Image (cartoon, rainbow over all chains, first blue to last red; front, top):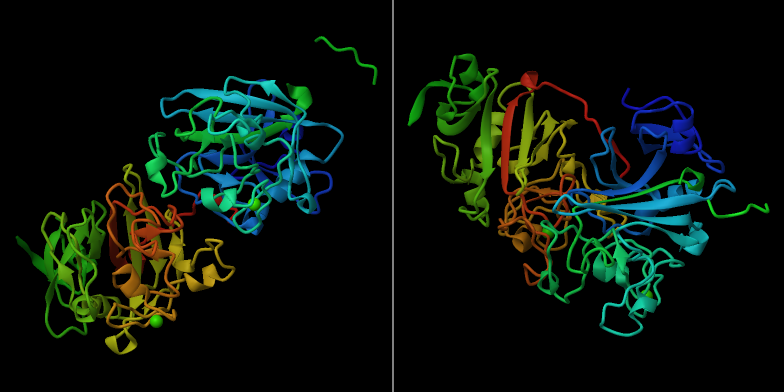
Length: 257
Length: 260
Ligand SMILES: [Ca+2]
Ligand SMILES: [Ca+2]
């Protein structure tokens, strides 16, 4: 009732078995030693998304250390109305279990009620040993734009090279892995795949109203929940959702093998 | 201005048909003299004796031991004023009979959201024990168990340094915390401090809720916080701390699974 009884490798597997209610389900990906709970989004078209990040009201402090970001934090709820981070370890187990690739959907919401998506095909989070590196093959489309591709903020020509995210390792204030002498995780106060910071950073500080400024932080860090290709760096989203689905769920190709 | 009914606490006053919230005299079993309390009486016959109220930043909570012992602020028949009833009275009421009391912490967002945290068998010890706070267990509530301690992640022992059960009371001029320094003096309040706090409803009132490390010279998280419902840099808009006999508490399970 509070936890549904259908299980599988992920939510798509669960939706396939006939599950049709979004809520909490246990899943045990392939190389997982033990099953764990996850929130599955299931729509009419039989698409079963496994949700791994959710922001919707700034009640959960996203300035957690490495272990926390690894294990997870926040709270799962049958209504999908709580903020959380499933945990790097779990995001890695799910994303790399088989030969079947996943697609990542970033879903964003305005303080004006406007939503936008951004898909990334062939998404994977590497193992801890490689600091949970993020990788995708390509941007599959979406009206939010491909901020993971870096952005030219105008502050420096090398901007796009330094604000891209594909290939970045995960960083937390206590485990810095950015292409920088400083610490993007500590100064922003979050855990993310930081470059010489970021163009899309859904784990930033939640600013009510969306609009924030250089005066909100002592050093004018643009540390809100941003997606530079959709909204300015000084506009923090109302809601974000990061979730994955087997790629096949998403015709001009000839299959050789 | 003051109601006629009286008793050992507000629940007693409710069982005697008091139907309006307001000021009432109560005389706990071990109390020598009766005193005024604000009683919250709902439509179910529950009478909550209120001992702390914050809602506009009018009263300054940086008071000393004697002041925290005797209480300060104002009581008002409308329940629109801020105060701290006094550790002595809170003590006399919580430890009057064998009957266990339950504490309800009611908080309010700057967005109109309200949440609660109930603790069972709530008690405030004698002044001799520096008014130590004790409760048996978190009886539920969507505000979360801030008193259990919180793992901010800054230090592995955060949870251990931020728990409140069994902590004595501290004011700037009477440090009884588990910290080398003075949580009370640094935050500027009186509370059951540990190596500071996970829940601290007597902190500084910040308009808008949001505040930061720059709000105070040394960067303290000294707002009205409840670490399990909102971030440490979120100061509540309103907070109420009230007690009712445990027998009146309707226990209900939550609908959230905590990952951490
Ligand atoms: Ca660095
Ligand atoms: Ca001390």
